[PDB]
Amino acid sequence: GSSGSSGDIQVITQTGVPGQPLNFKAEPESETSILLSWTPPRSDTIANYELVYKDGEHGEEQRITIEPGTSYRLQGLKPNSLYYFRLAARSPQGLGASTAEISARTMQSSGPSSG
Image 1 (spheres, rainbow, N blue to C red):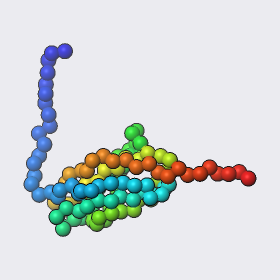
Image 2 (cartoon, rainbow, N blue to C red; image 1 turned 180 degrees about the vertical axis):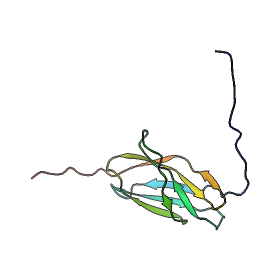
Image 3 (cartoon, one colour; image 1 turned 30 degrees about the vertical axis):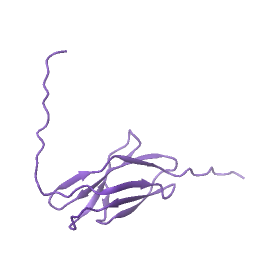
Image 4 (tube, rainbow, N blue to C red; image 1 turned 60 degrees about the vertical axis):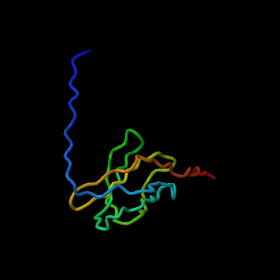
């Protein structure tokens, strides 16, 4: 109606975190596997990356322990299914920034011919 609050959470600025990677893209390497291509920032010291994925829109935001490199191979997915993905450099001092929410569609698996 009229009564307003406009009360936003006072984010905590703690200088000391890595900068989200660049050239971040996801491609369906397989029907049950997906490859991710990203570019690591200047920060050489990297523990790992956070991959928040969820089954479609009503999925669960699960995190995976990825190795501190440039790319990673994810396995164990459903065919012809949408799956969201989000990368975010993880430092031993504090979490960094998360890349743009990108999603990849698995390959269209053929039908189980009876015969």
